[PDB]
Amino acid sequence: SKKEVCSVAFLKAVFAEFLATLIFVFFGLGSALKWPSALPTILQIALAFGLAIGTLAQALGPVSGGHINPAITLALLVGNQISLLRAFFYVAAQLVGAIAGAGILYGVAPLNARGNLAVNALNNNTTQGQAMVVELILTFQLALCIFASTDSRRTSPVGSPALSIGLSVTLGHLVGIYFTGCSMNPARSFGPAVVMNRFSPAHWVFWVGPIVGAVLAAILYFYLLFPNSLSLSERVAIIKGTYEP
Amino acid sequence: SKKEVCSVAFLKAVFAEFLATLIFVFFGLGSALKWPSALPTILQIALAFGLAIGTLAQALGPVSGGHINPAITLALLVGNQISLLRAFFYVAAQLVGAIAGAGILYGVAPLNARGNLAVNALNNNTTQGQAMVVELILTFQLALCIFASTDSRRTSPVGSPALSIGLSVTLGHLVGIYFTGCSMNPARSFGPAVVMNRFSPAHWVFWVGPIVGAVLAAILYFYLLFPNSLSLSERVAIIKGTYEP
Amino acid sequence: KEVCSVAFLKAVFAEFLATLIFVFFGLGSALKWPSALPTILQIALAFGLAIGTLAQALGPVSGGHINPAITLALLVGNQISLLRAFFYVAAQLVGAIAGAGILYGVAPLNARGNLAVNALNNNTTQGQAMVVELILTFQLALCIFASTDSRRTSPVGSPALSIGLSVTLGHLVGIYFTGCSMNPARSFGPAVVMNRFSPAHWVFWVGPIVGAVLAAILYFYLLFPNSLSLSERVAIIKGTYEP
Amino acid sequence: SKKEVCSVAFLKAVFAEFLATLIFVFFGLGSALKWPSALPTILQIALAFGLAIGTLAQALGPVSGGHINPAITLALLVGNQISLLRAFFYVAAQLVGAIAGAGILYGVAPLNARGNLAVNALNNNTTQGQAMVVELILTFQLALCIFASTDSRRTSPVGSPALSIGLSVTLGHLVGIYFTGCSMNPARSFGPAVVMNRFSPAHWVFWVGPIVGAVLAAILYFYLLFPNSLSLSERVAIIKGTYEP
Ligand SMILES: CCCCCCCCCCCCCC(=O)OC[C@@H](COP(=O)(O)OC[C@@H](N)C(=O)O)OC(=O)CCCCC
């Protein structure tokens, strides 16, 4: 744990997530601004967020896990895949990341296109609870795809974990956008909300629905469909980050 | 088979065939809703349906084979690929899943969006028989792609079965939406048709079209082009669930 | 020899069958549906995805040419035999006719129009069009040849999807000039089905074939040649090369 | 090095780079013309430019490395793993094919759609600095993904390096077009310019932004994240072109 956190490997892994979430938020928000020029369409926006995740999973996945999402990091914590300290620093990183990325976009978009910087937001004729359950489901399917696409034990041809995973997030947007703007990711939500100093009463849903959805997926997969056999000592070791590097 | 049906893995498989179809119908109908906000276009809808199955195939395929469609399950039966009891259970789980999927969406979509909850629906301009033959074609190429994509034997690079298969679905909507709203799957149709007690006519088309095209592709793939060498009796054994290779 | 084989007979039926479905999907996806006129990207992905799928699905039976221009190219590149090429191109053409027909008999009157036949940009001359078609079919073919080279050591990802998106790419430019053929069978099929042969039709044979053949010679002779010996190359053509 | 510059393969590679850039400029420019017949939309264009690279990468990458972009060539020079001279002819070949490809479209494009020939051009609401940061960031993610997808030491599944790389350029277009019309490639910007005699006052952006972001991605990836054991001065044998005989 002191050994874990005090790796260059770890320092790198923490940096990869910051920079990944930075780049991810830049691109995702940037693609959804109401460019007067040409106003982004549902499909355009959904493939933009997804290709962002596919591209960063591919490019930086090797360095950290390519989590780029506090809900999937907390989930992976629940599923006994990472140490407590990895989860914590990752979430920080993703949140700091999300804010810097939103930061740079604010900085470079014309007055014209800045709008409210693509903050998530309800349909208005959509209720909070609804929002809440839609987001649970959007995130649930993503996590599942994620756990399945990176399981070292998987026997069937995996294809491209990166593109399956990114296109899974475009699928999420293809419905999510109509309910909430589509969060699926507490950091994607936090970022614009900070930077701009815009927080809606519903903002909590963008934290709750994603995390609960991911964690439900983590409990289903890792402990119901494909549990492994380790000792409580080894389980403990994971959480205390002692099990191994 | 007593030992087959009662096994824990089977109980997972049936759960997964249920879980998927539900999630698939959720995203499927949900992306197809006449959102006043921005009407889904046709590429929009097709990509959402394709990436749901692709996603789902990646995620729960290693659990059940991830049929997520009666036509295909039925066709793997006929092709001597699965046991009669995995076939009945798979179909039942699918039909119920689709119902719950239409069910959660119904309760989640705003009244302005709900509409007829994306039920299939032959175009006034087209004969049933007309409809019947395109849903035949549409599920024929899906079936072929699936079998080809998921065969043990195949020596040529398969790439991504899940993404290949997913985009097979998408392709099918690019033509299919124009005649029937693209069925290619008895449960996707039966689902919404149930949550709304408004089945409509030609619905049979949505059963026999897909199932026939599926079955035809089994015939050709498994008995015409790439037959197996299973014993005359070995076949009965896969029918009963006692086969062991 | 070949022909007289259940292997070669299955192949050819594969090419017939694949072209059918390919043509059905391509054309019906390009018809003028009044509820929603098929857009350019929409159309490009229907053609692209059809080939992606058919090659994934039927590719192991035949090699999935689904294109007389490719087949001839392979011949020229010494990758297939003379009879192989004869019978396939044969099959593709009739398979395409078949596919246009099934669609013609199935599309609603208000949709049928055209029937998605290839057709020149009006402000485009046949020579202009000839070069574009050349080019469109050139990139596609070397996508094919590189993606099905057994000597390839670089990870090939998905040859099927790479090749399908290759088609898609051709449409995104090509549709604006010629409606994008890239495939004489594709253009031949609806034309037979609805008489109406264009005065530019030759473009739709010559352009795609020349461009593919150019790519065949580039890749198999200039880029990635084999050792195959004079007499052993001729056995390639006579459909008796083992090795 | 006369060792490699005089090789028949160097020859083939220098030439493929020419051929690939040519075809890539033909297609990207060609897709993005206004075309009154049907104005190309943003995603339409994002996909065209992307599938062009993913295609050409697949086709011609084993011949040359398929850089098709002076910014990524120079970055590969910066991060080591190509020689100075390979870099010179590659960048020379890219600029000539770009011009070569822009010319052939000019020759082929009908009057009412030619324009312009799809030159890059700042948003008038966009600051040259602003546009530069954006281009920096756009090529940075692309260059990062390229390096990650072509690293021989990579262990986790790479999926399709060609289609990832391809979808990465598509990603960068879905934001970049609204800003600079999306360069990410000095050669794409240079080609049409030469042919139309249009060097916008902000031309510098299309080179320096893309080349910085690239080099930056190459420094991080090669020298910080995934450093190679060797070192030392067999690095100058890299530069000199005489390494690993
Ligand atoms: C609307 C427009 C949107 C466009 C969507 C575009 C998305 C298209 C998706 C294409 C991605 C295809 C990915 C794709 O084709 O990936 C294919 C796999 C090949 O698997 P494998 O046998 O090498 O790995 C071992 C395997 N048995 C296992 O199980 O691990 O990629 C790899 O992992 C390596 C590639 C090397 C090839 C020699």
Image (spheres, coloured by chain):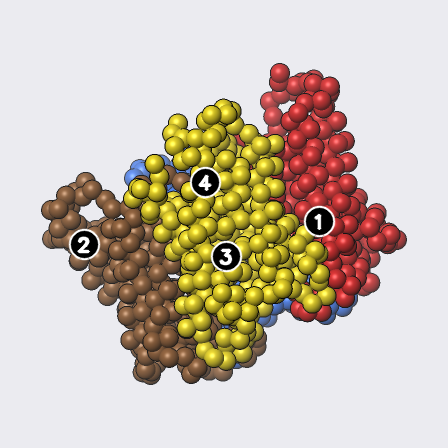
Chain colours: A blue, B brown, C yellow, D red
Q: Which residue is mark 4?
A: C82
Q: CA distance from mark 1 to mark 2?
A: 54 Å
Rendering coords of residue C4 (x, y %)? 31, 42
Labelled pair 4, 1 in contact (Cβ < 8 Å): no
Rendering coords of residue C98 (x, y %)? 41, 63
Q: Amino acid at mark 3?
A: Ala
Q: CA distance from mark 3 to mark 1?
A: 28 Å
Q: Chain of mark 3?
A: C
Q: Chain of mark 4?
A: C
The circle drawn on residue D25 is 1
The circle drawn on residue C109 is none
In this rendering, is residue D8 above or below A44? above
Q: Are marks 3 and 1 on the same chain?
A: no
Residue at the image position 59 percent from the left and 60 percent from the top: C201
Q: Amino acid at mark 4?
A: Leu
Residue at the image position 42 percent from the left and 35 percent from the top: C238
Element type at mark 4? helix
Q: Is residue A26 left or right of residue A240?
A: right
Residue at the image position 38 percent from the left and 59 percent from the top: B141
Looking at the image, is mark 3 or mark 4 earlier in the sequence? Answer: 4
Labelled pair 4, 2 in contact (Cβ < 8 Å): no
Q: Which residue is mark 2?
A: B83
The circle drawn on residue C185 is 3
Q: Is residue A145 left or right of residue C123?
A: left
**Mark 1 against mark 2, which lies toward the viewer?**
1
Q: CA distance from mark 4 to mark 1?
A: 36 Å
In this rendering, is residue B210 above or below A95? below
Residue at the image position 49 percent from the left and 45 percent from the top: C71
Q: CA distance from mark 3 to mark 4?
A: 18 Å
Q: Are marks 4 and 1 on the same chain?
A: no
Q: CA distance from mark 4 to mark 2?
A: 45 Å
